[PDB]
Length: 161
Ligand SMILES: *[C@@H]1O[C@H](CO)[C@@H](O)[C@H](O)[C@H]1NC(C)=O
Ligand SMILES: *[C@@H]1O[C@H](CO)[C@@H](O)[C@H](O)[C@H]1NC(C)=O
Ligand SMILES: *[C@@H]1O[C@H](CO)[C@@H](O)[C@H](O)[C@H]1NC(C)=O
Ligand SMILES: *[C@@H]1O[C@H](CO)[C@@H](O)[C@H](O)[C@H]1NC(C)=O
Ligand SMILES: *[C@@H]1O[C@H](CO)[C@@H](O)[C@H](O)[C@H]1NC(C)=O
Ligand SMILES: [Zn+2]
Ligand SMILES: [Zn+2]
Ligand SMILES: [Zn+2]
Ligand SMILES: [Zn+2]
Ligand SMILES: [Zn+2]
Ligand SMILES: [Zn+2]
Ligand SMILES: [Zn+2]
Ligand SMILES: [Zn+2]
Image 1 (cartoon, protein in one colour):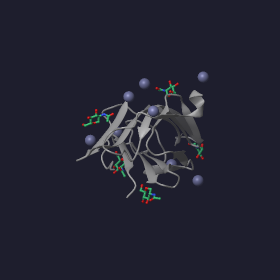
Image 2 (spheres, rainbow, N blue to C red):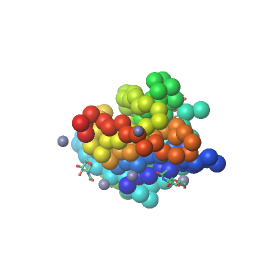
Image 3 (cartoon, rainbow, N blue to C red):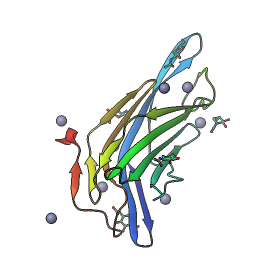
Image 4 (spheres, rainbow, N blue to C red):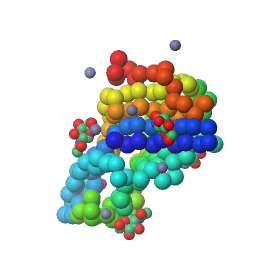
C-alpha cells in the first residue's frame, strides 16, 4: 500500500498512492533461468523523494530500488523515466544467480496528466520489459499540488473506462 505524501510549508506538494510488483527472470547455474515476483511491501523506504521536477524514489532491502520522474508543463506534466534497479548479488531474493551486481531496466513510457487533477487508476497497468514484467495498480496520484491541497477533480485512466 505504497503512500508517498510529501509536504512543504504550504501543504502537500506531491501525493502518490499505488501498488506495484516486479516479475524478474535472471540467469541461474548450469545454463538455466529463474523467474521470481517481488511484491513491494510497505517497510520499503521512499528516501530521495522530493517535490526542479518532483521525483519519487523507492528502496526495498539490498535488492531493489525504483524511481520515477514528474516534469511540469511538457503538457501539462509528464510521468517519465520509470527505472527499476535490481541487485542479483542478493541471495535473499535472487538465490542461485550467476550474474552479480546491479541491473537496470528502463521504461519508455511517457505519460501525460493535466495539472490541478488527481490521476486515478485502481486497474493493473502491465509493462513487459524483458527480463522484467512491471505491474502497477491502485493508483491515486498528483504531482505539483497547488495551494497545499490535493485536487478534488479526477482524471481516470481509460482502463477504468
Ligand atoms: C498528506 O499529509 C498532510 C500533512 O501531513 C495531511 O494533511 C493530508 O491529509 C495527507 N494526505 C493527503 C494530502 O492526501
Ligand atoms: C502481482 O500483481 C498482480 C496484479 O495486481 C497480481 O495478480 C499478482 O498476484 C501479484 N503477485 C504477487 C506475488 O503478489
Ligand atoms: C537465461 O539463461 C541463459 C543461459 O542459460 C542466459 O544466456 C540468459 O541471459 C538468461 N535470461 C534471463 C532473462 O535470465
Ligand atoms: C529524470 O530523473 C533523472 C534522475 O532520476 C534526472 O537526472 C533527469 O533530469 C530527470 N528528467 C528530466 C527531464 O529532468
Ligand atoms: C549488491 O548486493 C551485494 C550483497 O547484498 C552488495 O555487496 C553490493 O554492494 C550491492 N550493490 C549495490 C549497488 O547495492
Ligand atoms: Zn493491494
Ligand atoms: Zn487514497
Ligand atoms: Zn517521508
Ligand atoms: Zn538481501
Ligand atoms: Zn542483469
Ligand atoms: Zn535495452
Ligand atoms: Zn466543480
Ligand atoms: Zn474491467
